[PDB]
Every structure is written in structure tokens, then in C-alpha cells.
Image (cartoon, coloured by chain):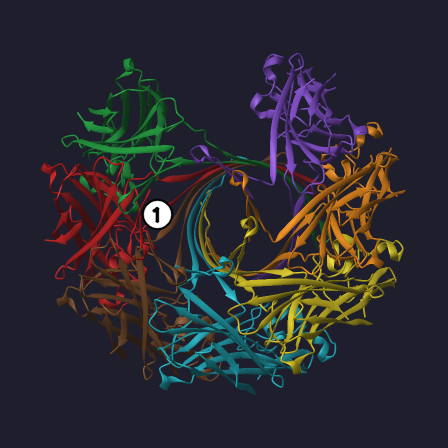
Chain colours: A green, B red, C brown, D cyan, E yellow, F orange, G purple
Amino acid sequence: TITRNKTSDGYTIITQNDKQIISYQSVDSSSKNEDGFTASIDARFIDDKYSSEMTTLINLTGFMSSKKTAINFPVRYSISILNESINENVKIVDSIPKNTISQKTVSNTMGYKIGGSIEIEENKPKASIESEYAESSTIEYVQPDFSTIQTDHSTSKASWDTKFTETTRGNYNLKSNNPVYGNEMFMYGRYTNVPATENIIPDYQMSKLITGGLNPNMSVVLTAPNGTEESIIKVKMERERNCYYLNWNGANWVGQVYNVDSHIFTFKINWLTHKVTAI
Amino acid sequence: TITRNKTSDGYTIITQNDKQIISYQSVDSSSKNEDGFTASIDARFIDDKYSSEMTTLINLTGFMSSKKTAINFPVRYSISILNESINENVKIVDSIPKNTISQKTVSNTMGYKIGGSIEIEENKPKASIESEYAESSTIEYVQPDFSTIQTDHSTSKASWDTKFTETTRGNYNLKSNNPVYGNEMFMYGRYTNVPATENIIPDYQMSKLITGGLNPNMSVVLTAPNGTEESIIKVKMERERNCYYLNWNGANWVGQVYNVDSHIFTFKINWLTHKVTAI
Amino acid sequence: TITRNKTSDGYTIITQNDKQIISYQSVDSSSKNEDGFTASIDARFIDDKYSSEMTTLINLTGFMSSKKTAINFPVRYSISILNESINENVKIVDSIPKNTISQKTVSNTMGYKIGGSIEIEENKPKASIESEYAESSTIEYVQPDFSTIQTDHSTSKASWDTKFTETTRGNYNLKSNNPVYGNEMFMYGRYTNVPATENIIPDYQMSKLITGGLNPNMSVVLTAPNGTEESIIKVKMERERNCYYLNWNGANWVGQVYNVDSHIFTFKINWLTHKVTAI
Amino acid sequence: TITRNKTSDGYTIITQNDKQIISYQSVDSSSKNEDGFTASIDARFIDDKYSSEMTTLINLTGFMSSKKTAINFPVRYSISILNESINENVKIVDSIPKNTISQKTVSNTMGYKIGGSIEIEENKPKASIESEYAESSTIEYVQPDFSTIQTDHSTSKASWDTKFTETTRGNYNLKSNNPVYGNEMFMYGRYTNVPATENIIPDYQMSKLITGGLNPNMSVVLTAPNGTEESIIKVKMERERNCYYLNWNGANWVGQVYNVDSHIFTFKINWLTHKVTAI
Amino acid sequence: TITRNKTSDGYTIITQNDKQIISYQSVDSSSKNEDGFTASIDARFIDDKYSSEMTTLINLTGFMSSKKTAINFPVRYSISILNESINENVKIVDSIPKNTISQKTVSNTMGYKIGGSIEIEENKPKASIESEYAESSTIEYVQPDFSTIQTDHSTSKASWDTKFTETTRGNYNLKSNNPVYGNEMFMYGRYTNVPATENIIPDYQMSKLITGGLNPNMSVVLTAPNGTEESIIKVKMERERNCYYLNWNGANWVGQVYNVDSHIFTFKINWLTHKVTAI
Amino acid sequence: TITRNKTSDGYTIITQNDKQIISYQSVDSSSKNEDGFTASIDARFIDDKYSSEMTTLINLTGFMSSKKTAINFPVRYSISILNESINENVKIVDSIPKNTISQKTVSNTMGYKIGGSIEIEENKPKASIESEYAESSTIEYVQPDFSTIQTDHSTSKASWDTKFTETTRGNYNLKSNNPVYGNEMFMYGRYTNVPATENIIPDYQMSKLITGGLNPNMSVVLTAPNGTEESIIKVKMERERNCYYLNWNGANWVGQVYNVDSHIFTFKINWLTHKVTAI
Amino acid sequence: TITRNKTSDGYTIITQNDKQIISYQSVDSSSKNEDGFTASIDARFIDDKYSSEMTTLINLTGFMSSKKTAINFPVRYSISILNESINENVKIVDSIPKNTISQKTVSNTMGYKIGGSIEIEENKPKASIESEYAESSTIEYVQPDFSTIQTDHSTSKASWDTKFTETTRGNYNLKSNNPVYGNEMFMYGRYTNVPATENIIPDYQMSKLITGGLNPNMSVVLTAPNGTEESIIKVKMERERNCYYLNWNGANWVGQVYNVDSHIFTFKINWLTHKVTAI
């Protein structure tokens, strides 16, 4: 699979190799500083001699910053990729993150005990017999701090999102309700008797994704028939947040839990020149 | 992919190989001894025949020393990388350290017990029946001594930082408060009755990052269109510290916890000559 | 990347390979027998066709012997590497040993129990109900016998040191104080009633680094602009020791814990001839 | 890196390869049957085109047999390698066995329990409340049966040794002392009432190194400037032993614990001819 | 490192490769059916262009069968290899099986408990306080069923042997002595009341090496100066056995424990012709 | 190590490679359906340029079916390979399955407890002190369901066999004897009160080797001097079985345990033609 | 091992490689929809230059569907492969699935406890001494849900089968019998008081092989002398099923457990043309 050529001047020889798979890579980035939204697209174009149609791989990356008495704290992120050239026969054949099935560990035990006691006192007998029976079981599983679920996949739209799950210490969630303390999420001490600002929980116990932004990684595969030259890609990003509130109720420290930011980014693809640009 | 040439004098043959990916590497360092701040930049330039634009990888390393009655002890470090040639279309497409999601291990068990005892004394019966029911659960997780969170990523600025977390022995933190002993961080004995200097805790129990400086490792990827010749990189470093205080309260040994150093370094990049220098 | 040549006499052919990275290695050693100090420097010179400046790797090794009623026993070692050609633009860009962050394992459990007992005697009832509640937690970590902390890194000086930590049996340290036995480090039996020399602890329980010397391993990277021919390297070594004392207090065996050796070694480097020598 | 030659007679072609690293190996052995001492030296000579000086690797192996009422039993071995050509600039740059730092596993737990019991008798109440608090910790480590410590390293002399540590069953050592049984090392039964010879402990429980000899493995690296032709190596071997004694004290079986063999071997090295011989 | 030659007839080309290390292998076996002794020697001859002397590797294998009221049962095996050409400068430089050092696992724990109970009866107080303290330790190790110890190594003789250790069930050994049952090795039931032959223990619980023979694997390295042509190797094999006896003592089943086979094999080696034969 | 040749017609070139080790493989099978005995021999012939004598590897495989109130059930299998050409200097140098040494895990623990209780009643003291001491040990090992022991190895005969060991549930064996239930091997229920045929144990609990036949794997190495042309191999197979019997004894279900099949197969080997056939 | 040829027209060169082992593969399938029986045969033909006879590998695969108050549920599957060309010297030398030997884990422990209590009341002593002794053991093993046993292997016939074993929850089997509940296999609740159809057990708890069909994997090796052209292979498949029945007995829910499908498939093999077809 080599092509060679000789020359008269100096007997120069120029050999070249004929390869099967050739890829090209281009990257593009864009940002909206007012919302703390940044997105990058990495595109790879694959030239294969045995394939019937053109293939482009569209990786996505970026940063969604998380913003931070009462404290505002995010609760949900959402990312969507839209194919806007459907009438040109450009199609979304695959998306990398997928849904999986969890595993649980189960154990069961059953036991029997029997005991006989003879007690000889001074010329006095006390015979006692005892019997016991027991059964138990154990369940084990593993719990992430955030959960990512693919929600849609079609010829034009792939949509993913993530949501708040639970705290590592105390196992509280957004729906808990203690009769006299309300919601004890992000509460240090019930009776510390210090200013509200000082009663909040140390930051390190909070998840990294609440203090700092999420870092997406998503990939989509596109194909097209021979000759296609242009394509538009739209990326939609949404963020939802809520607020936690803490106050006095007599001597008790009690709390309670009660907008949406979004932006659309556009990119243009050139298949013939192997180029990706912002638009 | 080889180019060969012959010569008349001695039939000398000079073969050369044509490769796809060629990299170049240059390093530069600088320091500010008065603050104990040192920074190094390692730059790699990548020449790829199939890529549409130039790529430079900018690794960063350095040393931030930690300085050390009352004892001063650091509490937070912060590093920021700034791209200052935005109007020339030089862009930050990627940053290596990222945010991750932790895992927790959860177990639950439930059990039942039943017991029957027959006690025959001298012509005296004593029948007793007992019943028990129990439930329990266990949570497991892993805790670092320091925590690093990425806080910003954009076209121009990437900012990281680290903060104090907790002690390995005693699990104290910066917000603890015992009613009669105050804060027991870095306290050997409550009643040792020795001079204040002697009551401090042995150094080895303290984290390495408090006794000795942090060693950063950060990487940033830059790209540019064809022909770009120059670029300015700014690196900002900040350190925050606080003080611990211990005194007598009658017979009790009690304690309490109550500036910011910074510097900006500048580097110049030459794309055409593959050079990095201080400035 | 091959250069070939033919000859008339016997048609002798001499082929040579053109390689990218070429390294050279030289080693040098020196000692001071009076103090039991020995040091060795291994230098590697790297010739790279794609690098902008010369690089030399300076590994360091050696032996610091530990010297050994009252017994003298070391407590701290310290090593420092000094670059003495700063005005010639020879710079220390990297040092291999670094500071790291430890990990802790944390577990928490909470449980509930309930029990009902019915006791039918001869026409006599005795109903009893019991209830229990419990909580606990466990912390795990790992402890070395000696600890090495990097204390300084700059353009000219890199300084490391090591210190005594604790005993494997008994978990004593240099600051412990029992009211009636004093310090029980290196004490076999409180009441053995044998001569002082015989009451010391068997040697094997002591750490290897106290009975025998430390074996350093340190590496430093140096770079220089084209044409540099000479460089001076200074290596400083210090050792600190203390004494343990044991005596009678009536029938009780009690103890207590109450100079500094140093030397500077010099080496000369020749970049052009790829040579390292003592000086 | 190939040299080729053609010939007229039969067109014979003789190709040779030019390699970078060439090693040579020679071995020599010697023994002293009266003391059960045997020693072997394996020497490797390295020819490197990029090294500034000659290097020889001197591995050492051998057998030191252990000799075996009262029973004689070894307690310490010692090996030393001496370089006797210091005035010719032949130097010991490295020795393979080194000192290492051990690891300990530490755990701590704290727990709380609370219990309330209500006991209704025939019109009689008996309310009881109980409370418990507990704390504990665990230490784990690993213990060899023999211990090897490097004791000296210098330009001329490297010295190692090994010593007896403890028994696998009973954890006795050379300094133990029971008031009425003395030392119970190597004692089967306190009251077996059989002849002294029969009361000794079965051999298999004893360590292999006491029943049979130690098998040393030691390596030393030597270097020299160009042109060196000869070198003398001295190997010193010492063995220390003691005796265990057992007798009657009324009905009790009691015991107690109360020379040095050595030899020097000589070897001659020839650098130019790559030869090692006894001398 | 290739030698090539051309020919006129048909332009036949015969290329040969010049290799550095060439080995030759020959095997020989012999047996003595009357004693169930079989031995095999595998010899490998190594031709190395960079070595100063000839080397031969002498592996050994074979079968020693174990022979089997009163039952005869082996207790010790012994193998020895003798070099009988010492005056020709043929020497034993190495032997493969060696002595090793075992490892033990040690743990220690200490705990404290405290408990307070308040008991309010009908106008009657019963205050009780309890306190507990505990300490414990654990030792772990691993035990083979047979043990192999190298006992001698010299210029002429290498001698190994193996001995009986203990039973897997019951942990008995050759020196145990129960006052009323004697030795309970190989005894099924104390009171089974069946004929002596029937009271023996099932065979599977016995070690494989007692029911069936040992399979030795031993290796010895020999070297010689240039020109050596012949060598004699002697292999000595010994086996020791004892007897177990069982009888009635009233109603109790009691037992007690109270020649040597050997043979010498001879082999002849031819260095020049690379041959091994029986003799 | 290549031989090449050119030709005039079409310039045809025929290259051949000269290799060191060449093997040949032939297989043969035979059966005796009346006894359910099948045997296969796989023979490999090795041609080595550096070996002094010819080598043949004789693998063996086959099937021995197991045959199946009173139930017949096998108890022992035995396989023997016989070399019948001893007078032609054809010898058995090696046999693959061998005897091995097992491992046991041993642990020991010792602990001390002490407790002091103070009980203040209404003006009544009850001081109690308690003390405890405990010791324990644990033994672990692994148990196969069948056991294979090599029993003989010589110049002419290699003999192996396998025997019944124990049940996975209940740990019974062939020598157990309960006073009132006899042998409880293969008994479902003592009082099920169903026909004898129905009281047998479900088949799955029985070992696979009793329900279905054993699958042997044995290998033997033969060597011979140059020129040998023929060899006879005899394979002997034996199987032993016994019977289990169950009956009523009043209301109790009791049991008790109270020929030999064999065949010889013959094979012929041709060394010169590399052939194996039945005979 | 290459054959090359040149040509005049365009100097075309056609090189071919001579390989040692060449394989051919053909597959064939067939089904009987009325019984849900499907079978596939994959045949591989091996041409080896060093083998004395032809070899064909016959893999087998397929699907046997399982069919599903009273519920019919399978209980046994059986597969048999028949060689029908015995008189042509076509022979079955090997079959891949085989019988194996299981492993059990056994542990034993023995312990001793001793306790002394002193109780000083108001001028009243109560000395109590207690003693305890205990022994225990543990057995571990692993249990599949279905079991496959090879039952026959001969020159013409290889027969395998599988059978029902036990339930994962409750450990019931086909022979269990509770006096008042009968067989509790596939029974949800004893007193649920819902229609019979509703009391059956949820499907997921049942084994996959009962709800869905078995997927066989079997392989057989055939050999033949040179020149063989045709061969017939017969595959026999059988399935056995039974029924479970449940009804009322007063207030109790009780149950009890009380045809055979088969088919023969035929395939034809062509050795010379390397073809497999249905017949």
C-alpha cells in the first residue's frame, strides 16, 4: 500500500503510504460571562475508504458556574444538543452517556439456640430449660451525590440533566420535615446562639458541584451522505436554583426550603473544508 | 513517508523520515524570595499536519511556602491563570483539573428474635417468653485532609483554590466550640501545667501542607489561528493565614481562633520561534 | 534518519543512525569518615534536538550514619542542595520529592432496639418493656515511623529534612509525661531490679533509622542557555541528636528526655566535556 | 550501526553489529571447611560508549553454616566488604541493601448507648434507666523472625549484620525473665518429668536460620578511571553464638541464657583481561 | 551478525546467523526397583562468547517411594549431591533451594468502658456505677505440612533434607504425650470397640507425602576452565521410617510411638561431546 | 537461517526457512463399550537439532463411566501406564502429575478483663470486683471432594489412583458409625415414612464423579537413542465399587455400608514414520 | 517459506506465502417450530502439513424453549451427539465439557474461659469461680442453580444433560415435604386469601432457565484417514417437564408436585469440498 517515485536529479526518492482511516480535528469555544456559561465543541471528521457515508464526531465540554439568613444554592442542571439541518439528511445516530442498571447485595440468616441449666443448691434442685430462635437480613448498595439521567434521544434532539440528591452527613433531602426543627439541611447547631451567618455549615461538607460548577462531557455522532457541505448545531443550557431559610422559633433554630437561567449557543460546521466555527 | 537522496562522492545516501506530529518543549522559571513564591511554566508546541490551528500546552508548577501563645498557620491557597491576548484570538479551550462526584456506601439490617424459657423448680413452674426486634444502618465514606475545587473557567481566566479541612486526630475544624475548653485544635493536654510553648501539639500530627508548602500542578490548553507570533500569560498567586491562641482560665487550658499575601508573574510566549521567556 | 557510506576497498559499508535524544552519565563520590558522612552525585546530560536549552539531571545519594544510664540517639536529619552559579543563569527548575495529602476512613452507625417480656408465674403477671438506642463512629488512618517534609524550593536552594515520630509499641513520643514514671520510651520493665544497662529495650524494636543511618535519595533538575561550560554545586548535611536518662526514685524506675553535626561538600560540573568531579 | 564486508571468493558477506552496552561475567568461589564458611563473588564488567569511567558490579553470595542440658545456638551474623585499593582511585559508589521505614495501622472507635426499661408488676412500677459510654483503639503491624540492618557505608567499607529477634510461638526474647520459670525459650513442658534431652522443643518450631545456615546476598558497585588493571577485594565474615541451660528447681523446670568465629577471604580482579581469581 | 554465501549453480544462497548464547541438553535416568528409588539428571551445557569459563547446569529429579496393630510410616527424607572431581578444578558455585525468613502478623487492642445506672423504685433510689478495662492481642502465621531445610553447601557437597511436621487435624506431633491416652496420632475413636485394624484413621487425612513418595527438585551449577572433558557426579539418597502402636488398657484405647534405607547413584559427564550417561 | 533458490523460467524464487524445533502430532483412540471404558493417546514427536536423543510426549485422556434398598456406587479409580520395550532402551524419564504439600492457617489469641463495681443503695455499700482471663485458637484449611495420589514411578511403570473422600453436607465418610442410626450417608430423612426408594438423597448433592465418570489427564515423557523404530505402550484401567443399604429398625431408619472391573489397552508407536496406531 | 514470480509485462511480481495451518469454516442451521427446537452446527476443517490424518471440529449451539391451579414447568434437558459412520473409520476423539471436582472450606475453633469474682458486702464475703469451654466449626461451599453432568463418551456417542437443583430463596427441592403445608415451592403467601392464580410467586425469583430456554454449547472433535469424503451426524434433543398443584385445606394453602418431548436432527458433512449441509 505504498506509492514510490524516483527522480533524475540526485536520484531523489519520495515514498508515500496509503492509509485506510484518516481523521481531522478542529475545536471551537464560546462564552457568556454575564451568566458564567462557557461551551466548547471538538469536532473530528473521519475519512474511511470502506464506509458508505461521511461521519463526524461532536464532543462537547464546558463550564456552568454555580452561584452562591437565606442562601441561594443550585438544584438542577440541564444540557440539550439540537440538530437543525434535518431537511438536509444530517442525522444523530448515537449519544455516548446512557442509562444503566444498579446492583444490590442481599443476605439472610436464620439461627436456633437451646440451653439447659442444672442448679444444685443445698439439697435444692432448680432445673431450667431455655430456647431461642432468630432471623435477620442485610441489604447493601452504593449512593452517588449527584445523578445524571438521559431523558431524550431522537433524530434531532438529545437531552440530559442532573439533579440534587442528598447530603453525605445526615442523609437529608429536599422533602424532609422534622416537626419542630423543620429542615436541618445546612444547619450546624440547633442551640449555638450565634448570629445567623455564623450558624451555617462549613463549606467542605457541601458537594463540590454546589460550591463549584459542573463540568459537562457529552458526545454525539453525526452522519451524512456524500457531498454535504454545511451544518448548524445548537446547544441549549439551563440552570435551576432555590433558597434555604433559617430563623428563631423561641429557643429553637428552625429552617425551611422554598429563577431559571438559560442560553442558546450556535456553531457552524463545514464538512468539505473540515472546519468548525462560532456563529 | 521517506525522502531519500544519493550523492556522487562516495555514494553517500541521506534518508529522512516525514512524521505527522512534531512537538517542541521550552521551560522558564521565576521567583520572589521575599514571599517564598516560585513559579515555573513548561510550554509544548504541537505541529500537526491534519490540524486546522496551532496548539500550545502550558503546564504550571511551583512552590508556595507556608509560614509558621499564638501560632500563625495558613488556611487557604489560591492560583489563577490569566490570558491577556484576547483581542488577538488566543483562547483557553481546556483546563485539566476538574470537579468530580463522590461515592457513599450504605447498609441496612433488620432482625427478629424470639425466646421461650421453661423453669421447673421444686414443684413450681415459671414460664417466661421474650421477644426482640432490631434495626440498624451504616454509612461509609473517605475524607481527604485538603480539598481542591475549580472555581472558574472561561475564555480568559481559570481559577483554582484549596482550603483547610479538618484534623486527622480529633476531627476538629475551624468552627468548633466547646463551652469550657473553646477550640481544642493544636492542643496537647488540658492540664499538663507546662509553659504555653510546651503545650503545643507535636508537629508530625499536623498536615504536611501546613508545615511545608503546597506544590501546584495545573495545565491549560491554548489555540490560535495560523501566523500568530506572540502572547502574554499572567499568573496570580494568593495565600491566606490565621492565628490560634491559648491561655489559662483558672485551672483550665482554653483556646480560640480569630493578612493576605499575593503576587503576579508575567511570561512572554513566541509561537514562531518556539520560545518562552520571563518578562 | 540513517546516513550510509560505501567504500572502494572491499565494498565496505558503514551505516550510522541519527537519534533524537542522547544522554551522558558521570558519577562522583566523597566522604568525611570522622563524621560518618558520605555523599554521591550522579549527573546525566541530555542532548535533545528539539529543546531550546541544555538540561542536566543531578541525582543525589549517600549515607549519614547514626551514632549510639544515658543513651545518645538521633532525632533529626537535614539535607540541603545549593546552586552557586546564579549570576551565570543556571537555574533549579524542579525537585522530585514533594508534599502529599493524606486520606482518612470514616464510618458512622446508629441503631435502635426494643424488647417486650411477658412473665407468667403461678397466677402472677410481670410485664416488662425495655428500649435501647445507640450511636457510634470509627476513624482509620496509617502512620509511618519517620516523616519527610520538603521545606524549601527556590531558584537557588532546595531543602529537605526528616524527624523522629513515635514508637511502634506503646505510641510514645518526645513530649509524653507520666506523673510517676516520667517518659517510658526505651524502657523494658518498671520493676525488673537489674542494672541500668540491662533495663534498656531490645534493639530490634527500635526503628532501623535510629540503629542505622538514613539513605537519602534526592533529585534536582538544572537548565542553562547554550554555551555554558562550568557550574558549582554545594551540598549541606546536618544531624541533630539528644539523650535519654533513667534512674531510681525509691522503688520506681523513672526516666526523662533532655550537639549538631554538619558538613558542606562541593562538586564541579563541566557541561561541554560532560564531566563531574570533586573539588 | 552495522559494518558489512564483501569478499571475492564465493561472494562471502560478513556483517557485524555495533552495540552500545557490552557486559562480561566471571565468577570465583572459595571455602574454609573447618568453619563451614563459603563465599562466592560474581563480577560483571560493563563497557559503555557514553560513560566516562569503567564500572564493575561485584555480587556476593555464600553459605555460613549454623552450629548446633545445654544447647549452643547462634545469635548474630555479620558480613563486611573492604576495598583495599583506595590509593589507586578505586571507589565504592553504591551498595544494594538499604534501610527502610515501616508502616503501622491505627484505628479508634467511640460509642454511646442508652436504655430505658419499664417494668409493670401487679400494681407495682419499677422504672430503670441505664447509660453507657465506651472508647477503644487497635494497632496492627508485621514482625519478621530475623532483622538485617546496614551499619556502615563509605568509600572503602560496607558492613551489614543480622541478629536474633523472637520466637513465633510464645513471643519470647533474649531478655525475658519469669520469676519462677526463668527463660521459657526452647522449653516444651514445665512438668513433663522426662530426661533433660527429651524436654527440648521440636526442631520445626525453630527458625530455619538457626537450624540451617544463612544465605547472604550483597552487591557493591565499583568504578575506576581509564586504564586501571588490578584490584584487591577483602571479605570478612563473623558469627556469634550463645548457650541455653535447663535444670530442676524442686519440682519446677527452669532455664537461663548466658565464642566468636571469623575469617577473611581475598580476591584479585583484573580489569583489562576481565578476570576474577582467588588469591 | 549474519554470514551469507552465494553459489553459481542456480544462484543458491545460504545464510547463517551468528548467535551469542547456545545451549545443549541431555538427560539420563536410573533406578533401583528393590528400594523404590529412581533418579534422573538433566544437564544443560552453555556456550557463551563473553564468558571466561564453561558452565553446566545439573537439574535433578526423581521418585522416592514411601512404604506403608502397628503401622510403619516414614519420618525423614534426605538428598545429597557430591562433586567427585575436585582435583580437576570442577566447582559447585550455586544451589537453587535456599533458606528464607518467615513473617508473623501481630495485633494489640486496649479498651475502656464506663456505665451509670439510675433505678427509681417506688420511692426508693438505687444508684450503681460500673467500670471496665480490657486488653488483648492476636498472632497469625501459616504452617506447612512438611519442611525442607538446606543443611550444607560447599565446593564439593550440597545436602538437603525434609522431615515430618504435624497433623492437619488435631495438631499432634512426634513428642506429644497425653497421660491416659498416650499419643493420639492416627487414632479414629477412643471407644469404637472394633478390631485394631478398623480403628486406624482414614487415609485421606494423612499427608500425600506419607501415602505417596516425595518428588525432589534440586539444581546445582558447575563451572570449569577451558578444555575440561570429564566429570563424575554422585547422588546419595536416604530414607528414615518409624512405627506407631495401639492397644487396650482396660477400656481405653492407647498408643505409642517408638531402619534406614540408602543408595548411591553415579553419573558420568562429557563436556567436549555434550553427553551425560549412567555409570 | 534461510535457503533461497532462483530459476530461469519466469525468475521463480523459492525461499525456505531452517527452524530449530519441529514437532509432529498423531492421535489414536479405542473403547470397550461393555465396561464403559474409553482411552485416547495423543503422541507428539520432537526433532531438535541440539538434542542428543529422540523425545516423544505421550498424553493420555479418556472416559471411565460410573455405574449406578441398596445402591451401587463407585469408591476408587486407578490408572497405570506400562512401558513394554525396556530391553530396547526406551525409558520413562518424567510424569506430569506430582505430589504437593498443603498449607494450614493458625491463629492464637489471649485476653484479660478486669471490672470494678460500686453499688450505693440507701445507706448500704456493695463493692464487687471481677476478673476474667481467656485464650483461644483457630485452624483453617481447604478440603477437596476427591483426592489423587501418585503411587508409583519407575523406568517402566507409572501408576495413579483416586478415592472417595467425604460428603459436602454432613461431613460423613466410609468409616462413620452412629450407635442408633448407623451410617447416615445418602439418607434424606430419619422419619419420613415413605418407601425406601423415595428416602434416598437428591442426586445433585452427590459429587459429579459419582453420578458421572472421571475424565483422566496424564502425561508421560519417553526418550530413545538414535534409530529406534517401534514401541509398545500398555494402559491398564481398574474401577472399584461398593453398596449402601437402608432398612427399618422399629421406627428408626438405619443404614450400613459393606467387584472390580479392569481392562488392558495396547498401542503401537512408529518413531521413524511418526505414527501411532491401535493394536 | 515464500514463492515469488516475475513477469515480462510491466515487471509484475506476484509473491505468495506458504503457511503451515489452514482452516475452513462452514455453518448450518435447522429448526422445528412446533416444539421450539433449534440447532446449529459450526464445522471447522483443519489442514496441517505435519499431521497424519484429517481433523474436523464440530461445535454445536441452539435453542430449547421452555414451556409455561397448576403450572407446567420443565425439570430436565438432555442433548446427545451420535456419529453414524463408524464403519468408515470416522471417530470421536474428544468432547469439551468435562467433570470437575469441587472444593470445600473448613474451619475449627476451640476456646477456654475462666473467671473469678470476689464480692465484699457489708461484712459478708461471696466468692464465686466460673469456668467455660467451647468448640465449634464452619463449612463453606458454593451452589449453582442448575447442574450439567457429562454422562457418556465413546467412539460413537457423547451424551450430556441438565437437571433442576433448588430455589435461591427458601432452599426447597423436588423432594421436600412439610407435614401441613406440603411443598412450598412457588408459593407466595400461606394465608393471602386471593384467587389461586394470584398466589403464585413473582416470575423474577424463578431461574432464567425455567422462564426461558437453555442455550447449549457443546464441542466434538472428529478425525479420519486420508481421502474420506462424507459423514452423517445425528443430534438428539429431549426435554422433560412436570406440574405443581395448589389448593385449600380448610384455612391452609397447600401444594404438591407430581410428558417428554424429543426430536432427531440430521446433518451431512463433505470433507473434500469443505461443506456442511442439512439433510
**Would you say D67 lies left or right of C66 here?**
right
Write down the residue under mark 1. Answer: B143
For the C terminus of chain G, the image quarter is top right
Which type of secondary structure does the marked residue at label 1 adopt?
Answer: strand
Most extreme residue toward the bottom is D259
Name which quarter of the figure residue A188 lies in.
top left
In-front residue for pair C245/E8: E8
Q: Is residue F264 above or below residue E40?
A: above
Q: Is residue B260 visible?
A: no
**Would you say G17 lies left or right of A87 here?**
right
Name which quarter of the figure residue F250 lies in.
top right
Q: Is residue D268 above or below residue A8?
A: below
In-front residue for pair A117/F139: F139
Specify few, some or many for label 1: CA neighbours under 10 Å numbering under 14, 14-19, or 20 or more.
some
**Would you say F38 lies left or right of C249 here?**
right
In-front residue for pair B164/C216: C216
